[PDB]
Image (tube, rainbow over all chains, first blue to last red; front, side, top):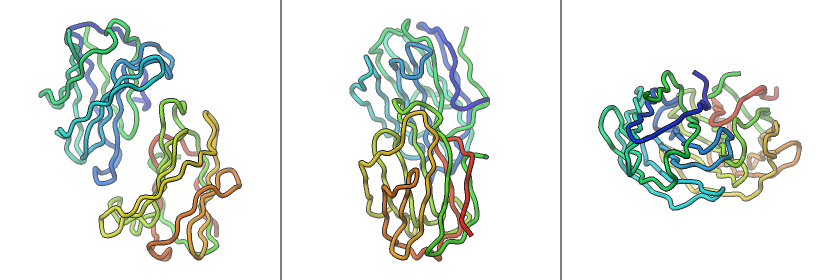
Length: 136
Length: 136
């Protein structure tokens, strides 16, 4: 599976985006993971949901609307384990995205852009990928 | 050329480390480049010279000594061009590392660890690589 990974999607309440992968280096060297829900296939399109894991440290979430980054949302929750494969499950709810790590919800991000605007997901930074699945 | 790229090295005053590559995404999405001069082959070994480019934004330099990150050094110099292949040339001088971008020096980092302690270089984050050459 190629990284950066870019896929066309369509999402609504009830959708899940499942991502399975492995960080490329040890947590001590601070690998990152970034998942961006874009409004168009173009890479510089707006981002309804930006989810960036600083492995072993913190998580940052935001949106990019009309080319401008908005209010940052940080989390200290860090369920990811050094050297381990992770399974990310991003649930689309009516009010928010909910990010599950290995089956439990650890991050939440209220919708700022309607989820019907999402047309693309890009997964990138310091991971290998074995699975990217949108429910249907 | 595989990324993350890890090579055994030996460096002294007069050495140059040349790195040619290309960012994996457009500058608007803030790709990174990280070059770490390590004291051992192990990834979690100390770092005599940590050089991290936030493409289109800034550069951060530091050292990691006895597993602890030291004083950060930032630069606003940004000679890198969006979408373009870059040629990084890291000159080892008696007093410092000097980072050249496409033939001109834009960053400098005084030695905190003796350069004879460097045994490994790792190049990683959001780039493809076509060249990694240590002068000899």
